[PDB]
Length: 318
Length: 314
Ligand SMILES: C[S@@+](CC[C@H](N)C(=O)[O-])C[C@H]1O[C@@H](n2cnc3c(N)ncnc32)[C@H](O)[C@@H]1O
Ligand SMILES: CSC[C@H]1O[C@@H](n2cnc3c(N)ncnc32)[C@H](O)[C@@H]1O
Ligand code: SF4
Ligand code: SF4
Image 1 (tube, rainbow over the protein chains, first blue to last red):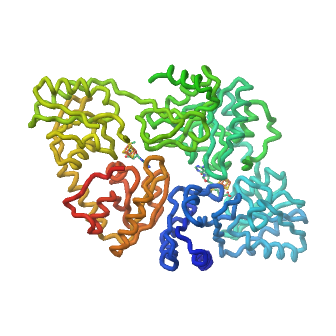
Image 2 (tube, rainbow over the protein chains, first blue to last red; image 1 turned 135 degrees about the vertical axis):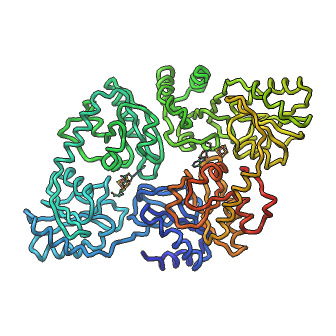
Image 3 (tube, each protein chain N blue to C red; image 1 turned 180 degrees about the horizontal axis):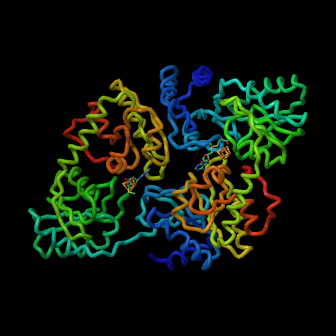
């Protein structure tokens, strides 16, 4: 990533103190970057040592005690006074993986989505698809993120476009799964780190979640989990869910925490939990919890306030 | 503890929202207590789910969104306007351990110190020591109770006497008293009813090795905790400047929890901990790189003679 701009920014503004925040994969570079900033500018650097899961997870205590917080690795989320997002993009060629998925397309209007690592390469991919003879749309998502076509585990607005199928560019199965479910459209996952392209079927995902719903039908006491992280806090929803719970003869207790981990939930024995924090906790960490952990809408289905056929992906709406 | 004073407090103050914070051993009670408050009052309850290590670790985000935060298991400290502290007094008998410690006494004026759980039983212990024919004194804001010591606070032992009896379990508090005051300390455990003189020579030798391992270090991480009662950023900035004065480099790392996992994420050779002093001592062998107290870091830098090492107090 572009360290020269960071130094120029600091050096132009005569920053007394500078803050650095890294996602877990980038922390190994934190000390090298702080060295570069202290060597080449006059600012003192404070490093954030908490786990950081994304731009939903800004260290606002550190931002409020430094002149500028550089948050690395993610597209911007929200609107912060003195937080500067440093994007950190990937070099990997995605066009070989794009052409691979072209042989699986069964429609002519193709929507393109990807993650922040690859978003600067979508236009290239859009022109390959268009020369192959197809139409290609890239929707706009979070307006506070400079690049369109970007999806998050909690945000599928870049997939709400006039198109027939989607090519998702990236690794991992969660995002194309969520798009498929949120759009009811066919999603082809093109992994550029493998030069392979496969269709994603959400039926297996949907069966597993129906199993957690079924598994919680007998639950009487629910822990409703709230996170204080800057972009994950949904207390208003949590209080509605408590009221819904009580309306159906069940009991919910609101548990407010920072990190949402199986170990901390194990300390409060309830029959099931409802996670209003990061939606990916519910899915990626499902098997690590000692009792069923439900999205807010799955909870509604468990109590009767929503029908199974209306189950939507959990999306971050604070 | 007293549920009835909690409910009375909630109803008289007309609370609509109440917070509960517990240490890890008491968290298994959180749901029962929340249920009791919701059944017997009009308040809605929010339970803090974070780990909580003491009255140094108030959940201030929760406190800021409720009318009253009940904090269980520690004595108060600091001054938070809407935080009520609900102490957990131990009711174990300490007098036999006191009587067992009389035999090891060498002097005539004895100081008494203990942890917060036993602090209401020190008067009785004082009478016993008096009847034995000795003088007994119980020394006196963080450690708000007479005779109470904390891992980060030994002011109750800054009292005029020749010898100390520590009543409680563990060796950190009596070791700390012995290092802070250079007096003889007898530790009297009321659960086992045993008493032994505590001598710091082996502890200091162990701390000396971590200083030795850290003198070779190129890059220090200077740890600051944002916890309400552990935050020492000013100290961190002083340490960073003094290190630089000696041609050594430290970077400040600001975090909430201070764990070996979060520190392994960074490529520093050694760490200076400005947060809870017990982390440095009790979690020592769990860290990949050596963790120092501020005073041990001063020794590594030649700012402080090894002979003048002292306990890290908040
Ligand atoms: C890999 S990151 C999400 C990747 C990226 N943010 C995205 O757009 O999909 C997701 C993981 O972060 C962890 N996580 C997120 N929020 C958390 C929280 N509040 N407490 C503990 N873990 C959290 C969960 O384990 C979850 O599986
Ligand atoms: C509760 S008694 C002191 C212990 O609490 C834990 N502890 C105290 N403060 C912190 C902190 N800020 N982060 C992580 N652990 C802590 C450490 O293990 C210490 O040994
Ligand atoms: S999926 Fe979870 S970790 Fe990723 S941005 Fe959304 S809330 Fe944050
Ligand atoms: S020893 Fe640590 S945990 Fe105990 S009160 Fe002092 S700072 Fe808090």
